[PDB]
Amino acid sequence: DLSLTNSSLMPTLNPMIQQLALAIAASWQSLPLKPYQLPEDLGYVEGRLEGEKLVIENRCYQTPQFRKMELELAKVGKGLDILHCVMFPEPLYGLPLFGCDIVAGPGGVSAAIADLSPTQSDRQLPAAYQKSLAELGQPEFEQQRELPPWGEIFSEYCLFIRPSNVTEEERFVQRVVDFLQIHCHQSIVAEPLSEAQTLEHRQGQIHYCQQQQKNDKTRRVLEKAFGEAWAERYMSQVLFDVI
Ligand SMILES: C=CC1=C(C)/C(=C/c2[nH]c(/C=C3N=C(/C=C4\NC(=O)C(C)=C4C=C)C(C)=C\3CCC(=O)O)c(CCC(=O)O)c2C)NC1=O
Ligand SMILES: [Cl-]
Ligand SMILES: [Cl-]
Image (cartoon, rainbow, N blue to C red; front, side, top):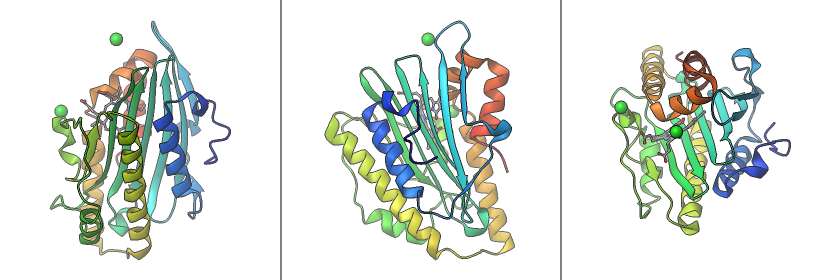
């Protein structure tokens, strides 16, 4: 569950990943949660082929506004730590997609990504999100990274950095907390949309998932531990299921 107290991975993960996992779990803890059953009720898996072992822990929930909320922690061998999180919105409410991805090695966090990603056909966040996000101001980060082409799905507020130091790690985590606070609040003030609008939002979410599946960074890690067929099933059915 979300206490993370029973996590075998948590104690061994990069400190920024630990703080983000805690912040996400704390954001969700008091929501009207129900468990979301993943395919094969996956909650914990390990695999190895010729190289290092991959270990994954999944914690997945749903609420009336979020069809599926995944907080996944993973580790390859002793080096490589990963946090994956997506809140998949229920299209009826028209909320954007919260996501973040953190990858860390022995030399520190290599990649930190977070976004509230659009589902509207115009590729814009809803007005209230645009207002609340603009009010946060532009955060300063020394080592910005350019998104790959499939990353067109991310909003203009997307963060993609290599944190330079602890101050930046903490600034990034605080901005994710700010995104979550906005998202939670908007989830209370959102109404059921029209059938045509619900359809538009569903289409945006489907596109997001199809584009995320183009990420070979994820795919290679999965393939090196479990092989091609397993990785394809995991990406298309567990991580980024097309609704
Ligand atoms: C088993 C799960 C899982 C694995 C194995 C994983 C691996 C992974 N993701 C990466 C990058 C990345 N990850 C993302 C983004 C995301 N990825 C997401 O899963 C989500 C929800 C977003 C955004 C909200 C982007 C944009 C990159 C950079 C891709 C690139 O450089 O080509 C990288 C490269 C890190 C680096 O270049 O420093 C690895 C190894 N991420 C995972 O989540
Ligand atoms: Cl691409
Ligand atoms: Cl390699």
